[PDB]
Length: 158
Length: 160
Ligand SMILES: [Mg+2]
Ligand SMILES: [Mg+2]
Ligand SMILES: [Mg+2]
Ligand SMILES: [Mg+2]
Ligand SMILES: [Mg+2]
Ligand SMILES: [Mg+2]
Image (cartoon, rainbow over all chains, first blue to last red; front, top):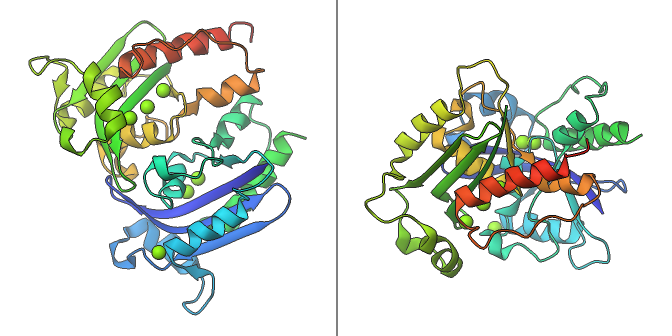
């Protein structure tokens, strides 16, 4: 059913160029990939310092084409499966677009992928803002960040 | 405090070209504009059928530049005032990007505009999925869309 995710990307007010994606299923499965298709030269200051250095070394199989990431996610999210898929992220409007654009325009999103991502911050605030683990060491690694989202959600719903 | 909004747009897997935006405040105030800058030619069948027909005539003052719409919104959302700005939309991920892209990069969004839009669909499900009035036939007009969201938010929360 539930997947927690995060993306890193280069966004210029016009497009969102996907750097990486981390997704963690409530059942414990984890997916992380980094795109071979974004242009590192086009990254602004904040990304160069905080995002770029934390990426896998160049020879890692974690590096995948946009097409591989799409096919990886269709398998990882079980899009042909029994269960209803429910996507979650923390302040994920841009993340939601970044994920969806792996498929193309919204019309080309697979029929079982939700057309919205639930907002963890919204749930957090609606439960009166309960005390959370402080920020992990490596924030801006999308998988670490996606992990911490699931941790947060479990706390709030315990 | 709370604003409810909707955007209409041409989205192609690459960009989100803003057509119109409708915003309604909890205090009764309303804003609506249509961008002079999208290219009607690029629109798909759906946007040709359901969106373009509801737009104001060419002479309407509702047609504005993207620059004018930014300035209008900075005023309307009371960006320099002391209330916390809360934004709400129904299934608003692309809407949130469309709105925020009026300021360019996320970098450049006024500090006082929140970095996320609250998701009215999520709220609905949370409180038990209570039965809602039907959507207006007028929907697909971003202002009508935004008013209706405000109405749904009122009904969903009416015993909170
Ligand atoms: Mg992100
Ligand atoms: Mg590819
Ligand atoms: Mg996020
Ligand atoms: Mg909309
Ligand atoms: Mg539209
Ligand atoms: Mg809306």
